[PDB]
Image (tube, rainbow, N blue to C red):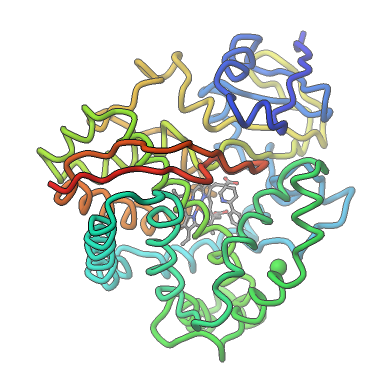
Length: 393
Ligand code: HEM
Ligand SMILES: O=C(O)c1ccc(-c2ccccn2)cc1
Ligand SMILES: [Cl-]
């Protein structure tokens, strides 16, 4: 019934060039079995979307990595939002929704846009930059920790902790095990900054604590919800912005459309999230025997979703391998779908829009002038280095 494949979606060969293997996974059937890790997989849009929108059957409380929390100990206390099912998930979800709300975006937009314009101006003075370290990393590092209300000391732990979190969703391979081995200094830093005394008033972190009054969360839950934003809100945006810059360098015709209408900035970032999804894969666990696309999956089985594959599925998208900044992108799963759909997507979009708007208004060309290096992660997709020359407009 279910085809068995030996493709390892957590191998460097797969990270290097996942597209061909993803077509193989999509075309083999709606549900495959991956013998390498003894998990089910779904690579088509329809099944990925269906799994995401059935949290009762495909739960998150048993972890969204390979590890099954009913069988193995989590490497850190479970997330109160990501690794929770309704109804436990509902109230921490509503709090983060209100912290990361439209009204909060109105308060940070001017500073985020000023910082993005200032960065592009700074980068234009140097001409030849690394679009990862000097842009995709430097810009969110200059707005997000300040938006959280973090102190200055110790921010070098932020990206390492994030890379650890997303590597840890993988199998016990060298990427995951190495990350955990070096994790103690990053965990200590992050956990300490999650305490209310260490969070600046007016920031995202202090606002989470300020919601402990309402009956939605208690004070003992607030540090873990701060930890959620420090886990999921930095490295994802770095890879998203890097993907957008990468796309604009590979598709100069799309950079030229963006220059002619900077108001396409928000959709050009959204298309980059569909085209080069920063988070390529993660898991659900079945809570019972379920039929999916004509196949029966037993209870307590891990199901690997290929989000980047669903976003390139020609059963859903026309010309899926083309970066199109006027594409109707609604429905892509780059931010998830359903009750867990990225609660910080307004922050991601704001960061990405104002950066691409700054590029649209100030940059004439983006040419790759050096070797492009990929950054390897069990679930994140992004570049290690992207040497580009920026031609000022
Ligand atoms: C390009 C940027 C981003 C991408 C591609 C992305 C992707 C995702 C995806 C796919 C999920 C769903 C996970 C699941 O269903 O198991 C998710 C959830 C989440 N994201 Fe994002 N994210 C981004 C930016 C952010 C930012 C900026 C924040 C916070 C400031 C954030 C915080 C969270 C949190 C807390 C969750 C858990 C929500 C829940 O379980 O209900 N992410 N993200
Ligand atoms: O609550 C946390 O700590 C946390 C929340 C969300 C993520 C995540 C996972 C997969 C894709 C995107 N984001 C990771 C951690
Ligand atoms: Cl931790």
